[PDB]
Image (cartoon, coloured by chain):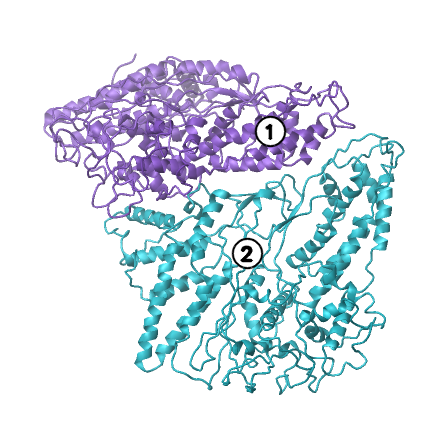
Chain colours: A cyan, B purple
């Protein structure tokens, strides 16, 4: 989370100004006035949360789910994007299905020996699996996935015959996806949309015929199984193609949409008869939520020639062949505000009344439960590692988190900065805005922190707007991978309040390849010390989405969304998951701390695991990397930074005594507040163990250096604030969130403030 | 063995003061006075001695014994504790039983070829064993053990079918366990308690069904054997779990016990209806011997929240599910004093009468027989090495030890220091205690010396109490692994004399997480120049266990315990044992010695094996590392150190001639005494061979340097004391106990003392 001036936001978060979504900079800040209105309505739904396992499992093969998986891993994987992955899949499909000699060997690994298929007899000496290893001996995939699926295909056609014997199970986790963003991602979605039928044709048709030729009872089959399989499988590859270009089909349908949206001349492009409203594309006229796609479309590219245009087509088929209707992906689909139904909102602020502090945010989780495991692997190959939870720690650490959910009630937490608003009087107001006030998005942090990219660097990248060109396919674009969502954020809850629309193409002087965002008249109070666009007249019109909110009521969020950990152990007690690795090793930390009793050190430390009381050291337990909370606590941390900076500056001059004590008074309980909650972090499960062992180490150190004489230090306040805050902070260190610098900075905060109490306790 | 002041023992062996078992240090030495009495009665039995072979053997598989083995090796192994070992076992059990493709391969190694299971025909071409190698090809264990057991499982279900053909046998040794100690060990015992049923569910149920499906006569089975086996085996894995947490269940039942023990407020924790005396937990009310578990429980940890508390539970099941009733382990179980029935006791001492010398000890072994072997191995893999004893040496070396048992009659040996007591007059007594007097435990030495850790370093570690943090999982904690037993020592024979109890929780000023040991009123003589707690009034009350003994009568031990070497060769003539390696290589020593006949050297040496008269050099004979005796002879050695130090100081000043000659007189025969017994060490079998060869080497050296002229040196006393004491000391060197420094120090002792005789010889 960060902040920016309202009047100067283009001079501030210039990239974030939506005008930036277009190549606009100019003397002019886009906008103007023009024409055609329609609230763009019905946005694609909420891909957030909803994490769960899925089962690849059966060779009966559902292409659909597998597609979902492809996009899933693709975003989650080591190789963007889905597109190239689909190419690679087709390559593999050639190398396998279109490469018959393999199949001879496969049947050879099955019943193969001599005079196959050993007449009418059964005998299916196979785990599904053993086939999988044999294919693993064949061409490696960077991303096997389908390497399972091809086996699944082997099962599907060998299912009618007596080789159902192997049947085990296969499992894989989801992966959270954003708003969801970029049209390139849609490109992935449409090629995947092809995969739905690029694959299913081989996933289906198949054969009920041949049992195993029958030929009572059925049947002998030399290479004939491999024969009938592959040659048909290759044939299935032939009908598969999808023909139609990925980026092209989206480019065109987007073209027709955006120029439909055009107030300035559609010209030869136009609404027409069967050119449009073909009992579906008009439903897209209702799906105008995917707006922004046109934005980057001109931005990522430029002119959007329909090139395979035709005029019968399309219409005809291509818009019909649009992805969401083929429904792969976290492409999701829904009405309006439900995606906004996780938007916080607090006008706060006063007298002016509008501007100095108006925050937004999101309601969120703390299902405390979090898990860890051994990576058992019945056979070496890749990462098909079975794992079982480690409940003995897994519960109590989660139990350790139980108060913590009552702590940092993020909604209530927002109230914190809102409370700051009255600081500092008195009223400005025209001379210096206004303020960002608003963003502090848990979502933007988690989206990037999930890849451990650290979002915070991306933040400033949206401050200046321009990407800092960290040229690497998993570096630079990933930053931008967020920025899209970031824009995608405000627009959606800029829908509600208000369905005001349009705007114009804003050609400027260069160059008319198209350039049209959206406008929002909303409705207003009669005073405008906020927004460069003075246009108070009745209401702002308005060029940029945020100002609507800037003129918006606090409304106070409905907002309920809060995720949940997947059950995992109940299934991986049977079957392997594959986001692993990712989840990592993973066991810090040795948090030593000093106690400077008069002119002496007596630093102590402790070896994580026995805080849990378990013994001894564990080597290979594997905690996840829980998300969500990181964003909260970070926001909490950084916002404290905003806090003490503001207040300290206030006492530095404002000015005028009646206020200074107020803030410096204010300051105190702020810290005092945190003080209190920090004990809840610790001495209440399980950091009491921490203070316990610390006392042990320190007194025993007294004895070891000799005297325990001075060692009254199990006592009061100063040492107690020391050890306690250290403790809760410490289990918090054992918590996988917030590093360490936050710790020293935190004690840096309390240390001037006062500490006093004596609150303990 | 060592010594310490009685009044100042907290300033001395501060760790040993039981108050140290709690975090207590303070201005105050724990104690005070309070309430609720009940002698804590019925201690878990005597795991000492009782060494013997056990047979893994049959695939009929007894989980119980195997469990015992797991704890056994665990303490004895390269990886503490049992807990992690059980985890690793579960991991392996996944990697094996829950990993089906393996089993296909296994049947393939059995009858596997084609169209399995080759109809109704028998043919069981297998040694049990060959399977074991095939599984060894699979995932390695650091600790195979169960790797055998899984094979045993293969046998158990393949037993109904014609594959009983392989049946050989499998064997493994015990391992001595202590008092026995720490509740973490109990944690091992409870997870092992799970193993009893974590394992047996797969060890049992199994199948009588299918013969081999029958299908007369029965049966064909492709992967169907592996199928039915593993899938059921995995299913058996599912019912296995044990669910309930290791450390938690003990933590809770211990909580209820200790707070039941609480004189200070139980508060919400309380005795109640079905909360307690549920026809068993009350038997634990009678099993209050496992006291101390609460002690370290607060010490190792802190607050003992019952967390899975409930109130129905537990009660209900968990205390029922306590380990000793599931009886794994050397957990052992018994009435009172039998564990104490190996406690020596000698008040000695005089006039005062109580304090200056009051010793304790233990009755002990010398079944002289000790053995050595070749490590024959029919096939390379690990250490399944067959061994046969080497009787020709093995008997005579044992024969060599035969007098030695009559020597060093440790009970009679105790009399030595007791005899020292009259030295030195005259009576103190208040000004300087008192003395430790008491400990010199064979047990504590052997417990650590078995791992060749050398206990003696641990000794001083209990002098200062604090561990010196030699951070290594098989270093530091192992020290502490002893210290527990060490405390565990005195308490038990602090039971008898007297069943006096309670004590209070001793919260001090920090911190009430619980802290309650035990107290002992006993009954006394009316004088107290012993114990800082003057409380003579009728009797001491008393804060620490040792003082009871300090006020105790000599009583003189019943005490009979003395172990025995296992028969070994009679079984390893058939089957491999697996404590091997451990037992080591193992053949020192080249003990050269000089004879400084006037102004000339003539040093001689001899090559161990021919002392036995055998020829030639043996490469690979493998003596054990006999224990027990090491502790005796060490105690003898160190106590001589106490002896000559004391006496020499006495002549240095005490003071007053009548005493000095006494002690310096005393001194003489002490040495004279040892002189005599040292000949019994040697020239009576088999060190006569040593003096023989020494004479050979020396006279032949005379001839080789030329003249044998001066060589009368097969003659008298001085040279004879030289060579004889050297001899007995030498075979003693060949004896695997007492190093070498002891030798030079020993001759250092005799050399001033006088030597004279002429006793020969």
Label 1 residue SS: helix
Residue B589 position (above or below residue A649)? above
> Few, some or many C-alpha atoms within 10 Å of disc 1 (few <14, some 14-19, many ≥20)?
many
- Position of residue A362 measured from the top left corner of the image (x, y, whole percent): 52, 65
> How far is the residue under mark 2 from the one under mark 1?
42 Å
Residue B166 place in picture, x, y as percent: 65, 20
Q: Quadrant of residue B399?
A: top left
- Chain under label 2? A
Q: Residue at x 74, y 73 (%)?
A: A257
Q: Nearer the viewer, mark 2 or mark 1?
A: 2
Q: Chain of mark 1?
A: B
- Vertical placement of A367 versus B31: above or below? below
Residue A203: x and y, percent? 78, 49
Q: Position of residue B97 (x, y in %)?
A: 62, 33
> Which residue is found at the position 20% from the left and 46% from the top?
B27
The foreground one among A171 and A266 is A266
Query: How busy is the neighbourhood of tag 2: few (under 14 within 10 Å), some, or many (20 plus)?
Result: some
Asked if marks 2 and 1 touch (Cβ < 8 Å), the reply is: no
Task: Identify the residue at image location x=65%, y=32%.
Answer: B230
Instruction: Name the foreground residue: B53 vs A11.
Output: A11
**Would you place residue A501 above or below residue B442 in this image?**
below
Which residue is under mark 1? Answer: B150
Along the line of sight, the residue nearer the viewer: A551 or A248: A551
Q: Quadrant of the C terminus of chain A?
A: bottom left
Q: Quadrant of residue A537?
A: bottom right
Residue A67 visible (yes or no): yes
User: Is residue B712 shown to the viewer in this render?
Assistant: no
Residue to which mark 2 is pinned: A563
């Amino acid at each position: 989370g960060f902040n920016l001036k309202v009047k100067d936001l283009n001079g501030s978060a210039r990239g974030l100004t939506q005008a930036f979504a277009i190549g606009e900079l100019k003397n002019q800040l886009s906008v103007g006035a023009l024409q055609l209105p329609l609230q763009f309505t019905r946005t694609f739904s909420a891909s957030m949360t909803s994490e769960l396992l899925w089962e690849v499992g059966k060779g009966n093969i559902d292409p659909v789910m597998y597609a979902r998986l492809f996009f899933q891993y693709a975003q989650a994987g080591g190789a963007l994007s889905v597109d190239e992955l689909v190419n690679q899949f087709t390559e593999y499909h050639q190398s396998t299905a279109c490469n018959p000699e393999i199949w001879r060997k496969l049947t050879a690994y099955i019943t193969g020996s001599s005079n196959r298929a050993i007449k009418a007899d059964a005998v299916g000496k196979v785990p599904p699996t053993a086939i999988l290893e044999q294919l693993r001996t064949l061409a490696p995939s960077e991303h096997e996935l389908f390497h399972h699926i091809t086996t699944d295909f082997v099962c599907h056609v060998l299912s009618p015959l007596g080789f159902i014997l192997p049947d085990a199970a296969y499992v894989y986790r989801v992966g959270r996806t954003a708003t969801y963003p970029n049209f390139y991602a849609l490109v992935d979605c449409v090629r995947a949309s092809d995969l739905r039928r690029m694959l299913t044709a081989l996933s289906s048709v198949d054969s009920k015929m041949l049992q195993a030729t029958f030929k009572a009872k059925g049947a002998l089959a030399p290479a004939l199984i491999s024969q009938h399989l592959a040659n048909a499988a290759t044939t299935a590859f032939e009908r598969s193609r999808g023909n139609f270009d990925a980026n092209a089909v989206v480019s065109s349908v987007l073209t027709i949409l955006g120029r439909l949206w055009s107030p300035s001349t559609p010209k030869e492009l136009d609404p027409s008869a069967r050119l449009r409203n073909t009992n579906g594309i008009d439903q897209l006229r209702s799906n105008l939520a995917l707006f922004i796609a046109y934005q980057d479309m001109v931005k990522q590219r430029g002119r959007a020639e329909v090139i395979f245009s035709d005029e019968e087509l399309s219409s005809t088929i291509i818009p019909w062949f649009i992805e969401a209707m083929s429904e792969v992906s976290p492409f999701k689909l829904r009405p309006i505000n439900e995606t906004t139904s996780y938007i916080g909102q607090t006008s706060a602020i006063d007298h002016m009344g509008q501007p100095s502090h108006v925050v937004v945010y999101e309601d969120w989780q703390f299902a405390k439960e979090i898990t860890a495991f051994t990576p058992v692997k019945l056979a070496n190959n890749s990462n098909q590692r079975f794992l079982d939870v480690e409940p003995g720690i897994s519960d109590r650490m989660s139990a350790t988190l139980a108060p913590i959910g009552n702590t940092f009630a993020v909604s209530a937490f927002v109230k914190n900065r809102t409370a700051v608003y009255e600081a500092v009087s008195q009223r400005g107001t025209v001379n210096s805005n206004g303020a960002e006030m608003t963003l502090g998005f848990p979502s933007v942090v988690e989206r990037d922190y999930a890849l451990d990219r650290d979002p915070m660097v991306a933040i400033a990248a949206l401050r200046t707007g321009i990407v800092d060109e960290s040229l690497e396919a998993r570096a630079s674009n990933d930053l931008k991978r967020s920025m899209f969502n970031y824009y995608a954020a405000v627009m959606h809850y800029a829908v509600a309040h208000n369905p005001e629309v349009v705007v114009s193409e804003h050609q400027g002087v260069a160059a008319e390849q198209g350039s049209l965002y959206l406008v929002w008249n909303v409705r207003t109070e009669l005073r405008i010390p906020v927004g460069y666009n003075a246009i108070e007249g009745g209401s702002i019109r308005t060029p940029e989405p945020l100002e609507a909110i800037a003129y918006n009521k606090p409304i106070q969020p409905s907002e309920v969304l809060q995720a949940k950990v997947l059950d995992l152990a109940n299934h991986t007690t049977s079957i392997h998951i594959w986001p692993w690795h990712e989840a990592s090793t993973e066991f810090a930390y040795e948090d030593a701390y000093s106690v400077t009793i008069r002119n002496k050190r007596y630093t102590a430390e402790v070896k994580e695991f026995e805080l849990l009381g378990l013994g001894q050291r564990r080597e290979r337990v594997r905690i996840l990397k829980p998300t969500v909370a990181h964003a909260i606590i970070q926001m909490w941390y950084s916002w404290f930074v905003e806090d003490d900076r503001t207040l300290a500056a206030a006492r530095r001059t404002s000015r005028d005594d009646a206020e200074k004590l107020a803030i410096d008074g204010r300051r105190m309980q702020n810290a005092v507040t945190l003080l209190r909650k920090i004990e809840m972090i610790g001495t209440t499960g399980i950091g009491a163990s921490a203070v316990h062992l610390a006392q042990s180490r320190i007194v025993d150190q007294m004895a070891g250096r000799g005297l325990i004489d001075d060692s009254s230090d199990l006592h009061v306040g100063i040492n107690r604030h020391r050890i306690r805050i250290w403790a809760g902070l410490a289990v918090l260190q054992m918590m996988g969130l917030l590093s360490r610098s936050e710790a020293e900075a935190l004690t840096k905060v309390l240390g001037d403030s006062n500490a006093l109490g004596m609150v303990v306790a």
